[PDB]
Length: 15
Image (cartoon, rainbow, N blue to C red; front, side):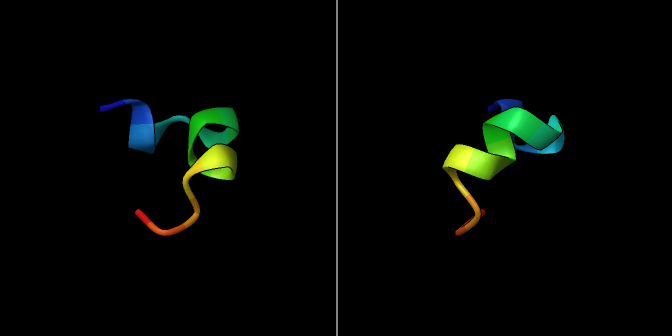
C-alpha cells in the first residue's frame, strides 16, 4: 500500500 507516501496517506489518513 502507498500509505507511506503523503498524497496517498492524504486520501487514507486512517492508515
